[PDB]
Amino acid sequence: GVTVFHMGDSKKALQPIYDLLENCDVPISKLLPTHVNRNVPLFEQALEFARKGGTIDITSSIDEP
Amino acid sequence: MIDYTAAGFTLLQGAHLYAPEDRGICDVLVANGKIIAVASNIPSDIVPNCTVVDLSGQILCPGFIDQHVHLIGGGGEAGPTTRTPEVALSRLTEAGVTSVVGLLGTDSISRHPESLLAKTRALNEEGISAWMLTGAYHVPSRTITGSVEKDVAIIDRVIGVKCAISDHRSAAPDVYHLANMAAESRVGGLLGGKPGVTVFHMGDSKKALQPIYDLLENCDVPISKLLPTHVNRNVPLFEQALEFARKGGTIDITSSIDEPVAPAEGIARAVQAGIPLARVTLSSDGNGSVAGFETLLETVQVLVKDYDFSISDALRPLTSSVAGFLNLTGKGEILPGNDADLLVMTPELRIEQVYARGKLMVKDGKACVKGTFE
Amino acid sequence: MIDYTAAGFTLLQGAHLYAPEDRGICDVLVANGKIIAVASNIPSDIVPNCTVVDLSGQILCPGFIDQHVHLIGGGGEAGPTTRTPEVALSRLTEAGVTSVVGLLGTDSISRHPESLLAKTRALNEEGISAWMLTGAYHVPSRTITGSVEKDVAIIDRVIGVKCAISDHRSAAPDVYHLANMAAESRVGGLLGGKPGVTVFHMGDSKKALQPIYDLLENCDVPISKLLPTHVNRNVPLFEQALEFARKGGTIDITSSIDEPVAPAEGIARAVQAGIPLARVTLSSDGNGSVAGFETLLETVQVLVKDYDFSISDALRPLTSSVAGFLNLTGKGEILPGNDADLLVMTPELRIEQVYARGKLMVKDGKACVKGTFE
Amino acid sequence: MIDYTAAGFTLLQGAHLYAPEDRGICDVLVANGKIIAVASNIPSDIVPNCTVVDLSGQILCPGFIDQHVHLIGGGGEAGPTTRTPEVALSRLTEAGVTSVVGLLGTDSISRHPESLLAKTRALNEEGISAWMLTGAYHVPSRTITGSVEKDVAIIDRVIGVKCAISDHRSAAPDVYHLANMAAESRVGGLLGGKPGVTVFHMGDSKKALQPIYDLLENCDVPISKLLPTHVNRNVPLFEQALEFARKGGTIDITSSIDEPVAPAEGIARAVQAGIPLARVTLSSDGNGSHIGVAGFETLLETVQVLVKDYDFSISDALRPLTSSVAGFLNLTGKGEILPGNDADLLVMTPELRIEQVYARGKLMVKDGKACVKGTFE
């Protein structure tokens, strides 16, 4: 019963997710952001997310940045 | 014969010169405390009474510039017994420090700017280069002349103001008082030809750099003036400091903190993050806590040893980077015109000799010039 | 023979000692105002000139520490006629108070900190232990030296600052002024080896503790420094105080208020709420209103009688809890080293004798040592 | 067994006591930093865990009270480089000093009253007893609370005020600002239970003590509250100093100055002039001012020379450093080794060289070397 988010390049990065956690009680262990390594600040935030309990998903098909 | 020793001519020859940018085996001619020549193989007789010194097989780099030292003492956070003593000249010159920026910490009741100013001037007379930051953790700042802007402006040794945020020992400053403070430091600096920076002592609050960002909104002080320190005190905050450095700001890492982010580990992660070393400096926060200055040279060594930084790149956060942030004209770099602040090291980076404005401070790794009462 | 009475040796033997933690029939050897021994059955000749006293069948516990007393007087909220008089030494020692924290209330125009400081010192000379809080309901605070931080720091008897919020007699303080005030008290405390607390007089506003929460956001002062009082003045507020105590903060209940939440009823509800008694203290707000100190001993009695608290647990909010909150080293607990502040009670908890720093204050339930002009 | 170590019982026995009054082979029982018994032959078992220390063949006397020490440092008269460092605990104790009064000097621009206070308290927590004089050379006085009267009244460790007169580094005060200054220290002293004394730094002006006599003419501060210092810095000032003591004043000689009147010679000339030793104090002027920072040795060296080259009794040589000082500054429980007083005693040899030092019951000097030191020494 997980939710997998396709991360884009918007500056807001993981913001939509944190807002969600504020607006309901879905455990953070069910949200999965993907393509986290598609841009540095999103990957930075990705690390912070994992720190709060989330599990991040990196995609091998992307080599930079 | 005629007497030319007034010029105090000294020639440092045959050393592997790092200025910090790796040059080769270069020679450095010094006169009147100034580096008047830098070109490989200089005549040992080019100038008259020249104290020629053989540095063959040794390293020669710029002396360290430490911008975080409680010169007149600090501490006191646990009663009057915990008030640390003032800093000894030899202590600095032995750690390879030739230029230093004094400041006050938490205690601004038994520690006053007039004393720091005095200690700063006493240091300059004794041989090294010293400046000071006005204020303390406290905001609004307890100044010398009545306003931060006036201090930075007319007190010759003040280059900016200090303060403390996101800490449990602050004065609980609000964005306006904070912004105003920085603006005064900035304006003052222009009027005094000072960098006019604002150094923020970082605490362990969750808020971290939020006040520094909040400040950017409410004023127009260039981000190149806001310097946070102790960013390596907690990882969550360090991470933000990096993001802050990625935006054009500079970050100061204290070599007196070894966890959760060690000094080297700090300078290292920044590079990996893709931050020009230009925006990264290393401070000791010496005589704080009682903190020492050994960790400055140790952070260089470990950087070249444990991590894979080069001698030149390792030195930067302790020289040119610092010099370029405070606009300390003529320092942190070995070129004709700049000050003869030099460090003779072994290939293993162990300070042997130290030169400050021409004068010899450390002879056999032990200062041979000391403060009046050491 | 040789003279040893200089040591003023006194031995309290055969009493049911509560320190407050229920020990058995323990003996307590006192010397030079200090408890130098606590172990059942001590020799009546162990030390030379020893005033041996038979307390068989009596209770022995630490004297009360009352942290809310308008020592030099208070009131005045209805003209100059309503200005209450200063506190009498015998009044305190008879209610079983051996350590007290003075403070000012609403009137800070005809009542000054210099006077309180003076009264505090006069009390210490007379036999008991006294400290004081700087400021008053008014914010920013009217201090002695110019700043709260400086007062708490260098005035030897100031342990923190007071103020008033969510009340119709405040100065309508805003979060910044409030936060700054507490931060100064906190920093000052560290510099002076004082608890550096901030005691908030609670009013009957709907806002209740909201300002104290608002403060936590805007600064980093530990929640262990914010002490609200009179939390039992209205139920809605009391409920919040409990939630506040559940978060690590301490709450002060005034024994001078009997509704809607009586003192005992207050200390009781806290336990039910699951709050370690450690975070609960009981103050009198004596000489306020004219309030008296009888209600302190009455809150203990009623707690052991009407409610089902034990003698030991009942005493805590009036001793160890208080002592541990202000860090009053050597008080609120009977152990070797601590001060000989003692209370001899009947099994029914009716103070018979009182000892303050060794000296005997109350003999037959009536003080035998009084202030200079009683 | 029951634990009585809290009392910190200690039995100093066998020594030849000087309290400073010549006693004989007397004993001294300490408990909780206080002297609780003084009498010959005290039984070693008299109290529980009593740390009995045999001072057989030793001299036991009261600890030194140094009322002129630049605790936070001084100097600076030849530039910021000449600013001396803070005094180290051990430097004092090893000199016999158990009680000290701090003051400021020429420099009150880079030296502050709040710094002297904090330090004065560091030393207190570290084991000895320290007090301080508000103000400095400069008059009016740069103070803590805004008024000299207020400092001497409400700041616990302040016991009076300092100032300089007849010196080329003075602030050039007039009899008015000088008299008002001494009056406030007097009143404030009364209010706070402090000596409320005024200590004058004597210079080399020919006028010598003139400013003082003028003050007595312009107000009613008792002459027993005025204390001229460095009186032995030039002969005619020392001459006048003697006349001053004759009219009731108490003079203060500084051991750190050897000419043109030595410390020992000064205390001796005083006696010869008929001044009671009670009105003669000796201070060190420690840590003020190669350029060299002044030390605390000359103090003991005065007691020694007094007994060895002048005929003063051991008991008499001690007075101007013990009973005399405590008396002038109303230092309760000090300068006297009698029951009730504090355990500030020094253990010496019959040659008057310190061996042990006790401050409020703790051992500061175990073998002529400090076993207790400042937190960063």
Image: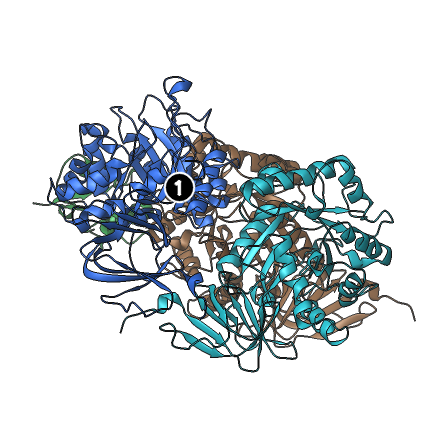
Chain colours: A green, B brown, C blue, D cyan
Q: Residue C188, percent across and down?
A: 45, 44
Q: Residue C56, percent across and down?
A: 20, 58
Would you say B147 lies left or right of C348 here? right
> What amino acid type is highlighted by mark number 1?
Lys
- The quarter of the image holding the N terminus of chain B is bottom right
Observer-nearest of B299 and D279? D279
Q: Which residue is mark 1?
A: C370
- The quarter of the image holding the C terminus of chain B is bottom right
Observer-nearest of C332 and C33? C33
* Depicted B276 relative to depicted D267: above or below: above
Residue sticking out furthest to the right: B1
Q: Residue D125, percent across and down?
A: 48, 58
Residue sticking out furthest to the top: C79
Residue D72 in view here = no
Chain of the residue that carries numbered disc 1 in the rendered image: C
Would you say D91 lies left or right of A54 here? right
* Depicted D231 relative to depicted C47: above or below: above
* Depicted C17 relative to depicted A7: above or below: below
Using the rendered view, name the quadrant where residue D215 is placed: top right
